[PDB]
Image 1 (cartoon, rainbow, N blue to C red):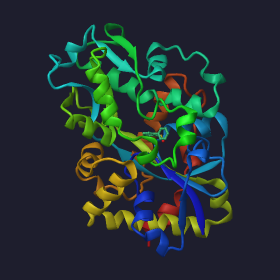
Image 2 (image 1 turned 45 degrees about the horizontal axis):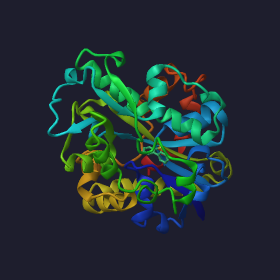
Image 3 (image 1 turned 60 degrees about the vertical axis):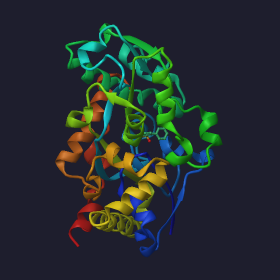
Length: 344
Ligand SMILES: O=S(O)c1ccccc1-c1ccccc1
């Protein structure tokens, strides 16, 4: 069987099972989304599509635009090097030092931080979701400033380009695929340039990108990766029709991901390498961006703790008016598959 797919620049068992051959053994082959069909990464508008990535796009799709297109198969928390980075030679060493400083943030993050979404509700799915992706920077800045007893009104918000948030339709359509290596090439190099421009004092970085940025001679004012309140819940979705019509296929898919997740625990280097190749980053940055032992946490989850993390992100979206009505996670989830896999 053939399924179209994609994954965000996050640790996940779908990519792992695919690259390690577990899916092939299960008689499943995945075809990654081309840049020309890239919007599906945000819209889920395909009959046999599966994605494992950030939770914001699917939450918006299910809760704001097209309820019912997907079912949730599992969750894999994400937490690693994260925060507002400054050059090593910057006199800024504590959160309090950010007072009155120039914080580079995406236009999307500025809308959220200002509490002024503008035309948000009128935007097409792609641009609309990109506004919501400004949430990473927004929450990170709020948490960071709390450390110095500061608020958003105590700093200068300066518009800059942020990876994954600023993705023009032309860039997407011109990209070979939605793999990080194609869509997000040399992120750290670009962020290092912003910090060297003399017009910004700090900017937000995370994922392996933060690992490579750090290597250029930069550091986070506050490493948000050290506090779980900065974690996100990567979600694994599949077209709802497959769940209802081809449960056998979905079960084989989930079984393969679980086996791949178990296998990953004893093949850390291979898992690091396949993620590094997929994202187009150094192998060392993967561990920094996802956590040193992320390979031990690849078996998908649907336990209450995992669902609570997903709910936490959903609440940030609701509070900030990015979502008006919440997605019923228990209804969205299709726990029977993962449950059957773990009971083998
Ligand atoms: O949750 S998202 O998939 C996501 C999560 C983390 C980093 C990048 C992206 C992304 C943004 C735009 C297009 C493709 C990926």
